[PDB]
Image: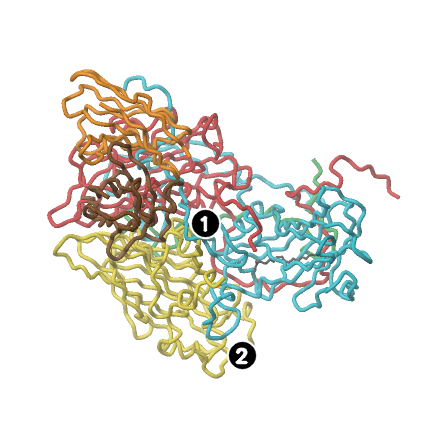
Chain colours: A green, B red, C brown, D yellow, E cyan, F orange
Amino acid sequence: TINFTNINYYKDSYAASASRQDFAQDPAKFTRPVLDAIREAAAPLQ
Amino acid sequence: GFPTELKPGTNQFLTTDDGTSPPILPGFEPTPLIHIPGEFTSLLDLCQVETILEVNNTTGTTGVSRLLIPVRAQNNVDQLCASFQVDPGRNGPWQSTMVGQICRYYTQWSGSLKVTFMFTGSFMATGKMLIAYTPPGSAQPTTREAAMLGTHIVWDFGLQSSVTLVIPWISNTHFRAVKTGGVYDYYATGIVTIWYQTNFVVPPDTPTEANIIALGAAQKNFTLKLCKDTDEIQQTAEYQ
Amino acid sequence: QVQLQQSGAELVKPGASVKLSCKASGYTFTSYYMYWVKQRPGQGLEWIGEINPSNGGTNFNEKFKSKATLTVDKSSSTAYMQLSSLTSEDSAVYYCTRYGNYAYWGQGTLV
Amino acid sequence: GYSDRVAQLTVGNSTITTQEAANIVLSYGEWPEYCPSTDATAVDKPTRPDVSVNRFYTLSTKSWKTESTGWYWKFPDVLNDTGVFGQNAQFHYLYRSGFCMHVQCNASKFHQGALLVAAIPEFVIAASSPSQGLYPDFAHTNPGKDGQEFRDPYVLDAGIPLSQALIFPHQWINLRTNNCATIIMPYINALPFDSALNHSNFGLVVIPISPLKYCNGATTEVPITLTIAPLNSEFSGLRQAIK
Amino acid sequence: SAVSALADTTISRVTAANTAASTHSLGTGRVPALQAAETGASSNSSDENLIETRCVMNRNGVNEASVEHFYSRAGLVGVVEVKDSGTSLDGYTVWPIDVMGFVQQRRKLELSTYMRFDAEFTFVSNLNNSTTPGMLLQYMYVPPGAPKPDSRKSYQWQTATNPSVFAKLSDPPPQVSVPFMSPATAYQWFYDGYPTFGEHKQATNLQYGQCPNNMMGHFAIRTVSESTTGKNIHVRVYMRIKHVRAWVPRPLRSQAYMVKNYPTYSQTITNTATDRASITTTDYEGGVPASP
Amino acid sequence: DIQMTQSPASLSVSVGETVTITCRASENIYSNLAWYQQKQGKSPQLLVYAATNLADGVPSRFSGSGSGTQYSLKINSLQSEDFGSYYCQHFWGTPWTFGGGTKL
Ligand SMILES: CCCCCCCCCCCCCCCCCC(=O)O
């Protein structure tokens, strides 16, 4: 119910707990790191 | 003196406890954060990067040759080229993959997998391969006629040298334990067998054996659960 | 095909050493371990040891550690076995075996 | 939605043509850029010798053989003694730049083999120990314009598996499919600028995964040519030239 | 007010990708399965285009695979032995802070090339027999350049400016927060270079890869004593990385580590995949076939 | 060291019968077994690799089966040239223990 968490008790921001509320996902910089976008249905090299 | 009462778990050091802790350096401002290319925020984004399967993980084979699936002109029809299981946390070809090594940091996994087979023969080398994924229950198919009863792709060699075998998420449970073997073969994903649909046909003066390079990765629906310690590297003494 | 051409027959006086050759052909030499098997006539086959033609890593049996030294000539695609401290129990036929996915054997060497 | 097989890379007075390309890789999705004032630390005005340093330098040709294990270069090192780049990299303490790495290996439609061409940021080279033999020598860490044959391509001479080197910006040269590999790499470092002599930002590996096989009568000498072009080369900290 | 912030503090589940229902596709020019791995791009083929899929409203959570959740776990980064018995009657130890001495933390960290994180260091200190008598210890962070103690009594222990934690062995483990301390904008587990200029022609190229940006100093630990206690104290240091940014993912190490600050493997290269009998051998018996 | 234990040390059957050799093991060798047929005078000829894969040129009369600890080589329709000594050989780990031998 009530969530009394993620409270920083110190004047320094790095004393706070882990940042576990900003989950991001961007696999394209590893999976599709190519200048030409290749449609899935398309034959890649034409 | 605000009345409090210490509960069980006081003084314990749980290693996975995200709590506050007193800063050693008051007023410390770290070095400014600049942009560095290549920031990853999820290990799932890394599991979706196709990495080579060590399908030739056979006794005797050494080095980069363990990464190659030999494919040659056959004298018979409907012969087995290669087979491997598709349990990403099992000892075998998937150990050489980023997905199979990030899986081993987790207890349970879920999602479709994907093997991208690239043919590395001559331009003049033609062939057709049946790559079958056999769901659980059946051992490695003994014939191609038995393998084609499962999820399979017929791969025609051509100008597009690569093909994707999407291993679909066919499971009874929402997640599969990365651990396999014993009773944990309840979570066996299945077997992938590569068959000669037609022959490996080359013209004269053309190499008769070539290599398929398999590339294992995860799909967009891949998921990992219950962070655990990996069994990859061991240690007997501190490193210096 | 994958042919392993071993050296010719050998007749060496006791208390010496002979260098047996194994000229591999038909495959990448640095891609498969080379194994040596000893067979005294009438007796069975005995495994001597292995050698990786990429780093010289050799793993012998507990009965051939101080009796067999394995080298490799990666440029010549040839493996070698120089049996030290020759005796009578070391006079046998010797093969060089590559396994990979199919155990390829040589022809043998009478020693 | 296709990738055209023909491509022309033009930077400076250099122009590279290919008719069997395989969709140039933009490393980590980020083009090379100059250092933003927000991320800059040094206060001297950087020199930007645009066309005299940002250009394709063809630097080394390695003969691909059946037993070849692979070669690696270090991007700043492979150019530290070449052209106006090397001179700017010697006269200046600070340097930052991206690169367009174009590896060229052409062979007939009767040759076969695949090369893994990867750009490895912070490619620390390992020493294989059976102490002096615990650390690699400078020839192996900074091979220069010539590059270094891989001792153990399986572990990338770094203890890390080659099969996972595809986590780095990579292309393949599969002889049946393409004769070139193009990786555009931005400047990756924990620092906005760094020494072009002390630090190698990226390794440039070309490892044969599928070995070069041909038949009798085919051209036996199949060369692999490395052509790299700095992109957005900045140099600061002008002083006496250091090699 | 701030009650809105406190309400939105629980980890909200982010779900994996749904599967859309697919049908048979009989036609030309639509090849979702033909790829080009030479492009360096992974396959964009979806299961909805290789097979006939059902619609799955996937409710599997993908949060635990975050870099934060992967790394925000305390692991052993240091074992310090405060020797005060036998030949080593020191009662103090100055420990070079390096998180690369133990396999579990080191391998997880080297997944990344650059990491920028704060840390929560915990010190688990006890005797040989696991007991924790009341023994005042001093845990002084000695940043690079600060005078290191040369005795249990030396003036450096006055910790006028250095951060010192005083705790008894009987107390719960001392735990502190360490910020991102580095002249760089990220720690660098792999530094392809040398810290200094020169010819680099030494027989022991010991300085290759040694970035002083990661060298964060020494933890100087002592028992607050006046003479030899006669007891050796084993301090174990656990780092919990937090507020973590990771860059340039790398292959997870496949070879057993040999030394702390260098990638260096044995000539006996272990295969990253365990061996099997042949390329057609699988370890799965399965059920009895109905009609072989 | 995973040692071997070949059950039938000798056998003599007629042309047409079916002999089945057995090759146990100390521990699970994971199908890393190779059966050889060595008639005294010639070189050891590989018959079945990986405990199931029939070698090239070997007649379909031969068949290898087994998994884990126990393995069996069967010679159905025992023709004339099927005599000699039959050795199993594990290639799992360090020792590479061959079989005792089977005279047939
Ligand atoms: C008051 C007691 C505090 C203890 C001191 C803690 C200071 C921690 C140092 C910072 C930790 C992260 C940096 C790790 C970098 C070292 C890696 C390496 O090069 O091997």
Q: How far is the residue under mark 2 from the one under mark 1? A: 44 Å
Mark number, residue D45: none
A28 lies above or below B171: below
Residue C85 falls left or right of residue D133:
left
Mark 2 falls on what kind of element? loop
Residue visible at 29% across and 72% down in the picture: D14
**F80 and A13: which is toward the camera:** F80
- The image quadrant that residue B189 belongs to is top left
D160 lies above or below A4: below
- The image quadrant that residue B165 belongs to is top left
Name the outermost residue toward the front. C14
**B88 and F57: which is toward the camera:** F57
Q: Chain of mark 2?
A: D
Instruction: Give the total of numbered labels.
Output: 2
B130 lies above or below C10: above
> Label 2: how many residues lie within 10 Å, few (<14), some (14-19) or many (20+)?
few
- The image quadrant that residue D88 belongs to is bottom left
Residue E133 falls left or right of residue D20:
right
Residue F103: x percent and y percent? 24, 24
Q: Closer to us: mark 2 or mark 1?
A: 1
Q: Are marks 2 and 1 on the same chain?
A: no
Could you tell me if residue E31 is visible in this image? no
- The quarter of the picture where the C terminus of chain D appears is bottom left
Q: Amino acid at mark 1?
A: Gln
Residue B3: x percent and y percent? 86, 39
Mark number, residue E255: 1
Q: Chain of mark 1?
A: E
Give the quadrant of ligand 1: bottom right
Q: Amino acid at mark 2?
A: Asp
Mark 1 falls on what kind of element? loop
**Which residue bears the numbered disc 2?**
D44
Could you tell me if residue A7 is visible in this image? yes
